[PDB]
Length: 187
Length: 187
Ligand code: NA
Ligand code: NA
Image (cartoon, rainbow over all chains, first blue to last red):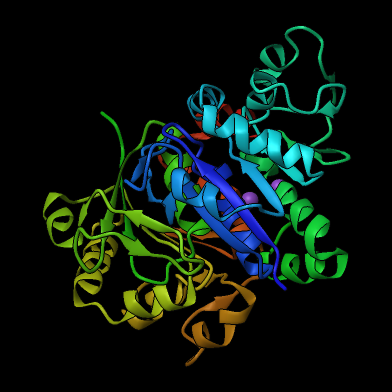
């Protein structure tokens, strides 16, 4: 029985911090749904890469629950995630069922917006620290990947492989993560 | 006067080894054209990420020349690049005008197919070494990024940031590469 991931893709997402997790998760045999926040239409990412989602979030959310919900990076993408009632509901449900929530770069700021995982140790992109820490609802970490129970966070495009492999390890185990890692030619 | 990059996107491209160079080059202020080998329609990459090109290769090739031609990774993507007469012509022209040619992962095997840069030191994904070395027309390297004159090669998804920054350094210089690198949170 394969694990399933929901990756929520909004306008202004950081395409590296989106594609790396999708691809690495699929290499691990996770069934990944790239769901467009705004619908099924193509999404213009932060550096103008245009990605066609697999489904609208509206449709994808009806096919839950998922073993992980992934919030990609991107400052404007995260702002869109933070403003979405649908995202709020998905994250609240996932938290309530004790399912993994993974967020990278500015992505974790949507956790703050939706009051998810307060009291957790988290990291973000350095430039998003102040936003994440407004109100002191989390404890901040400068680790490249941070995991506190079901809240898994990471810092930037350059930490995306580590972030993705941490998701794989959490879902499918250390051996699968190591097997997927080797052909990537990571340092 | 900004530098310009042509990134040739074929079905089966490795999406990480495509998006990382596009994004990093755009961060460096390079004008990047993501050109679809087969036309302007969306391209299904190796791990099912679907990317909409900026233009068809047919149109993009008429707007050359470019300061760099980039051949992304992906074993099936590289096979498609290797079979294309349009790619052959673009690479031959670029080589003749002493312009940079950058290829990652399986991408360099298209250089072999099109008889580009023979006698150069190159690297590839380890799994593509035998294909690249058929006939002994290159000298092989296990360096993560290899540059021999105008032929710039690299190994895999995990070397994509280094590859992209080497393109940036070649076009826009070391200082710009360092400036672009820092916010990526690379190790
Ligand atoms: Na990483
Ligand atoms: Na790299």
